[PDB]
Amino acid sequence: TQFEERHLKFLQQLGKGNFGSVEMCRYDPLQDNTGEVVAVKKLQHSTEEHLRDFEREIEILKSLQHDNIVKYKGVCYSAGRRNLKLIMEYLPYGSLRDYLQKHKERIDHIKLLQYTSQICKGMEYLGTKRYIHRDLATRNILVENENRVKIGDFGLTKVLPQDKEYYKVKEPGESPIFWYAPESLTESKFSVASDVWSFGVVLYELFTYIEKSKSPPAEFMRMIGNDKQGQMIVFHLIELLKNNGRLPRPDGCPDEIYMIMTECWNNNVNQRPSFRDLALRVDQIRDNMAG
Ligand SMILES: CS(=O)(=O)c1ccc(-c2cccn3nc(Nc4ccc(N5CCOCC5)cc4)nc23)cc1
């Protein structure tokens, strides 16, 4: 689980998010083109604040072993702590967001529910470790193959305090406000329940097939009125959600699946379903579609 920098060969950028960046690299210590391809995450700009966060993120990933969670391989200190790299398994199909968009004709509703189910199982497992993901979105879900997705990034994930069911955090800069629960917007409270709200948005995303005009940002902005910007956007979002304004049912989405989304989007934190009950309900719907 210790990787030397000089044996890591850059191939491609895979994405930036929050304050990290991920690259596809070949780890080739024999320098004979026989090493495996791996995903390598690093800080966009190394900083003491971010490095301490990055180290916690690494310990979180390292602590997680689950079919629907991306695998930790090691760390590359090599160029010093300030050039800390996280080495993970490379998943060849990319983000679910991108995959779905590219293969919309091939992916039916039965298949979307398989992915949904797998995402719920990953999240239930996180929950057993009292980890709050804080950034559930299709851009952070990865595709290993046609039958398996994994939660693939943990940049914003926090551990609950021992004595509370929520964690208050406010990081500098841009937050994915259109995936956030109301209490995360108004009070900065994150919880398993806020992750369930976001899971609702993931389910919406999936059933929209990532159609551009249908993304959560684009829908909420239209509902808010596109004649608004800056620090008044979150103010109007809070008001819209407080008055039970919600993302519409996607085109073709069955009502029983939309019901799941709307129940995740309860203003009452305590009435949102559990991840185990979501898996249950999704698997029943899956079966009734199987027949
Ligand atoms: C949300 S992000 O962009 O910060 C990000 C990107 C990648 C990862 C990541 C973490 C751990 C393992 N993997 N494997 C892949 N694979 C992968 C493969 C292809 C593509 N793309 C398809 C070709 O177009 C560009 C991206 C993206 C990711 N990506 C990862 C985590 C977060």
Image (tube, grey):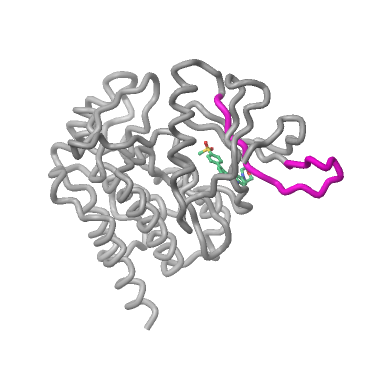
Q: Quadrant of residue 9?
A: top right
**Nearer to me, 26 or 286:** 26
Q: Is residue 40 left or right of residue 175?
A: right
Report the residue that reaches farthest toward the front: 2
Q: Residue furthest right?
A: 32
Horizontal placement of 62 versus 175: left or right? right
The image quadrant where one finds the C terminus is bottom left
- Magenta span includes 39: yes
The residue under the point 45% across, 23% down is: 52
Measured as percent of width and height from the top left, residue 194 is found at 25, 42
Q: Nearer the viewer, residue 257 or 18?
A: 18
Image quadrant containing the N terminus = top right
The percent position of residue 261, horizontal first and vertical second, equals: 27, 54
Residue stretch rendered in magenta on the structure: 26-43
Residue at x 34% of width, y 35% of height = 158
Quarter containing ligand 1? Answer: top right
Seen from the viewer's position, the closer of residues 70 and 271 is 70
Asked where in the image residue 39 lies, by quadrant, the reply is top right
